[PDB]
Amino acid sequence: ASMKIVVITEKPFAENAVKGIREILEKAGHEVVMIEKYKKKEDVIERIKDADGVIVRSDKIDEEIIKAGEKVKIIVRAGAGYDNIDIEACNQGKIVVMNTPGQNRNGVAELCIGMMIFGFRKGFKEGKGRELKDKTLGICGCGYVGKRVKEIAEGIGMKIKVYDPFITTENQVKKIEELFEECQVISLHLPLTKETKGKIGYELIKKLPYGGMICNTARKEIIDEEGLIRIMREREDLIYITDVAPTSKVFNNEFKGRFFATPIKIGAETEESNINAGMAAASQICDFFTNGTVKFQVNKFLE
Amino acid sequence: ASMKIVVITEKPFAENAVKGIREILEKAGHEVVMIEKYKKKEDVIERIKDADGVIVRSDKIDEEIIKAGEKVKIIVRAGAGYDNIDIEACNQGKIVVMNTPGQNRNGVAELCIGMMIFGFRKGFKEGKGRELKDKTLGICGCGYVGKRVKEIAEGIGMKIKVYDPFITTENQVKKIEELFEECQVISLHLPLTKETKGKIGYELIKKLPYGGMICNTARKEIIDEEGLIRIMREREDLIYITDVAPTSKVFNNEFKGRFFATPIKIGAETEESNINAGMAAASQICDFFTNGTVKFQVNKFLE
Image 1: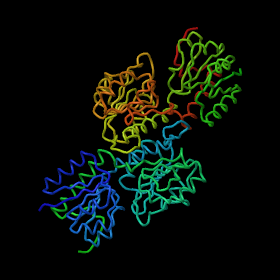
Image 2: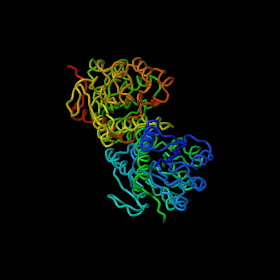
Image 3: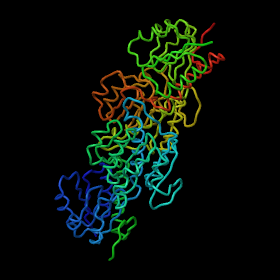
Image 4: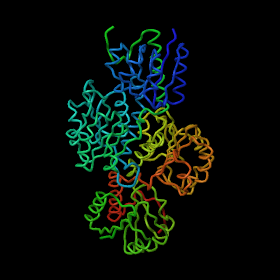
């Protein structure tokens, strides 16, 4: 029968994507309740209590919110990363958690390449820049975004090396240290896990050749900020460009001319990626309620 | 045998490029005099007096300067365009004018792609952007830069069409109107000539599909600024991004959010492109004085 699906997006989807979500879900017979640009946690807690399913972006979904959603059966993250969702609380609540792999890939990959050019070209200000062609790119974390970044970089004429902790691919280095020792530009795509939290720090970054640049379109917390600050102070040649702005104000204060962060994570903030991710999320909800389909489930629990 | 070569650059080459220029010319037994970051026209007029050869970038080289260089026998523009040089006055002065085709191509092509991404992604500010993938790119003028832009855009996954008044290539439209009709993104690469001056105006730009973007890494004067201003007020969806900042202050005043210009022309402001163009210029200068070679001469005169 009819289910209530709450869409929790502090950073709203494009109008056309919201249209697409509502069309898929209403036609399946469900109620859609939008919780957009909310400013307080109580907004979510109040409206989730009655929900059968949830669509979320990067919004924090913690134990308190999960426990409030007493009849939530499924949470779909429209997008890739799910570090924002307390997975263990969902396990205890017997809630299926899924994402929509690859739907955002092109918005993120195009931004990544754009930032690499911007970073190498003094943020489009005056001065002597450099070209990506004939430089070595290290793709740190290999999935849907990394493959697209590789394709674009190959057209640009970069030489490519790849690191990933779990999958096997071409041009792959065994150790992350090798990626930093051998590549002039690093593009970060690692998910945020226990293992990757604070992993990109002083000892890794110091290995970069002269004029090294790190582009981060992944997550802010994979950086060891103290460590990155320390090496950037020591190596005035290093550039850091990121779609996931650091917590520390030091970057903007001290490293003008070789640091840039977006005001908010805009990698997936395109019409095309919103449509892809939002509609995949709606389709996957509904398929779950119709057929019990659990493809792309990221957690696992008993009974 | 020994010649005096002056390098006239209000916008100086990278240090490594200047070193490369000196190496080539001083080995051939010639003298190199640098005229860098000058402010007054008199500075050049004075120092060109006893010059046998000139290397120049975008600097204005007019009749007064040419006549002051009484024994100048050659001027090499390190780069592509030569609209800055009074060709007619060179013809009467019996001075060979040449450029260094394609040496700058990658600096410009990478900047072009970077500006397209930047332009489609709100200048890396908050809000909903768009993706280049699956859009149609019109390459307006195809030479060395256009070919590279094409290669990179193909990796991005744009569909490609080309307009050029002279060459033959694939996916080529016969008339410029057709390019503006069929293509959502336009990249301008036309040289500035009598035929191209103010050619890109109201009538052409109006033809652009919804969400149209023009990227101009060519010359400011190929734009009919009054026409562009008119259509941009009428069509709020249109984006104009340029490496050749317009004369009119209206663009910056009125079109924030869908307009950007670099503070100076930075297309060729890279280590790599400076080395290529600067050293090619030096080699061509040296070749002219050694063997009288006139490959890449752009002008024609008798006697």
